[PDB]
Image: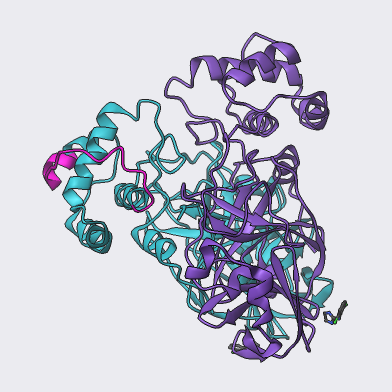
Chain colours: A purple, B cyan
Amino acid sequence: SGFRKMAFPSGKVEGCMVQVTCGTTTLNGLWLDDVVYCPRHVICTSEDMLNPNYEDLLIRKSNHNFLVQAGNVQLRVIGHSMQNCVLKLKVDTANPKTPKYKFVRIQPGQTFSVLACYNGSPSGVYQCAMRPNFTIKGSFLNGSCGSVGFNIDYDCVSFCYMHHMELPTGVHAGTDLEGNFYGPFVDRQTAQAAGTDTTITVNVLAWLYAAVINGDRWFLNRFTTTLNDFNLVAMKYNYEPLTQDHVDILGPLSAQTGIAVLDMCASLKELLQNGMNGRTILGSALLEDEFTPFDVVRQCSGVTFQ
Amino acid sequence: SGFRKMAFPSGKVEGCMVQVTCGTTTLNGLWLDDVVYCPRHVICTSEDMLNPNYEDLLIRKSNHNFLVQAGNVQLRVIGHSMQNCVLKLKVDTANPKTPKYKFVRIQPGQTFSVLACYNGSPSGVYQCAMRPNFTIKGSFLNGSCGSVGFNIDYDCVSFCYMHHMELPTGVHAGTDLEGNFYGPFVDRQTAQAAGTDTTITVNVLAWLYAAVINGDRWFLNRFTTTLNDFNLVAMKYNYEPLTQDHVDILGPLSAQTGIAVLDMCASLKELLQNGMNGRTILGSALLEDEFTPFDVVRQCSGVTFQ
Ligand SMILES: Clc1cccc(Cl)c1N=C1NCCN1
Ligand SMILES: Clc1cccc(Cl)c1N=C1NCCN1
């Protein structure tokens, strides 16, 4: 019993974190086999970041200018290339701690764990979600760039995020491990603002199921609804529209609890319309949307790794 | 920027988790040097747990009855002893992955990370606090017993909790690594109920400082208060009394922000008296008390490990 915002165990990623220094700048890189991945803005100075021409700035760089350090041990850089917004530094030693791994580009609403690092050193782990506006709400200070987001399935780390930028509103933007930004964001210090931070409806529903499984059930009501009626209310509250795909993925939690997906939607509708009146659900006073259906099953089941 | 419920990186503990089986029962143990620590109720059956005589049940056990497995590899048990509510199984191989470590008994209000495990395998990590009633609000299913709580300071893991019991109210109870329970709880399936879950006032204040550091400042007001006046309100809201020790430990956050501890107390007082009126602080609709002052400094600073 109990339901917690839970990150994946981070050891497998911890063994891949290194420090990358180019000139005056130091951030984190990810060492997988004989390649180190990091944000290409390592090559920029603070001034460069208003309008960088990365291809021109890169001309001035040679392998020996990228200082890569794994713990107290220096790695030899034998090649480098730019792929979209990441650098790939080829080193002469394969990381002996490389886990099984994959690079995934996730969809908005999907959750992942972040290992926050500074100077190649892990500082903490927490769970995040790719918001529908393609930001994440993280905890990143100067030097955390190159920290990564990831999921683990049995013994295989699926890397999905690399941290690059803090927007002036305090939210965060980054890339997949091929270096393509999530959303419209760019690695320049310019006027970029996040769109509407809509609520991830399927995740709220999943979390409500989690609550019922754990004895928080005061919000269950006598009502039901339809997809179209529920979405009229969702839209009004800046909730993502619920689709039949979404209903289907809630099927297993529906089956375990005996509460039809649309009956749960009617509970959510009343919560949106009447608030919580000072009550709590799973220790929260607002409706949590950073747990996916798979997350809820996983944690309510006890699936483990490696 | 950003402030998140953050656990310590878990790799160092992950390398210490093993599976312990005695008879029909399997839970987790902690392998440090040549000793494996686990809950002594591994030796009980489900029936035994109404009124176990551990000393008598142990007479029937020999080294070869405790099956200890590290990944796919069996460890040889060459001795065993009971220390309060934990077993210490001596094995013939020292864990090559033993980190630097200490056993600490923590005080209520102190926070720590938990690595939830099943069958010796890590499933997830999350941050917890030792409640003032000596429970923790965790996420533990059957087979998670022997999962541990810990803090990390530079390269040294301070183990402070081992998980043992779920109370009928869904909260959790456990021991330090010498096997003494936190609080009045016992390892028997009996009528034990948690006392009042009071709110950890110094932690709420710390978190409010964290909020100001990150731009959430709507709750700052024109008022101040005194320790005695604030505690009259704290008591009414089942908040722990604030002491001068507490004020002193908030000193550094006071200095960084320029907000006197007692002025912040006056903000907290108004929040307690008038609620939040549908607003949020650091993404929460209630007052978070599972971040210590040290936690807030740590995360707002970027301290790293090993
Ligand atoms: Cl397995 C592999 C794939 C691609 C490149 C290298 Cl160098 C590889 N070799 C190692 N990676 C981890 C230790 N050896
Ligand atoms: Cl360092 C120590 C302290 C106590 C007992 C043993 Cl067996 C020790 N040896 C090792 N622990 C980790 C690897 N070797």
Which quarter of the rendering shows the C terminus of chain B?
bottom right
Judged by its main secondary structure, the magenta piece is loop
Q: Is residue B161 above or below residue B230?
A: below
Q: In this view, does A269 lie above or below A208?
A: above
Q: Does residue A259 appear anywhere in the picture?
A: no
Q: In this view, does A36 lie above or below B140?
A: below
Q: Is residue A257 left or right of residue B164?
A: right
Nearest the viewer among A207 and B284 is: B284
**What percent of the width, then of the height, locates residue A98?**
78, 75
Q: In this view, does B102 lie above or below B263?
A: below
Q: In which quarter of the image is residue B145?
A: bottom right
Residue B215 counted in the magenta span: yes
> Magenta residues, as a range?
B213-231
Q: Does residue B105 appear anywhere in the picture?
A: yes
**What percent of the width, then of the height, locates residue B11?**
64, 70
Which quarter of the rendering shows the N terminus of chain B?
bottom left
Q: Is residue A223 left or right of residue A172?
A: right
Give me the residue at 75% from left, 21% from top: A261
**What percent of the width, then of the height, locates residue A162?**
66, 61
Q: Quadrant of ligand 2?
A: bottom right
| Labels in figure, total | 0
**What percent of the width, then of the height, locates residue A177?**
74, 62
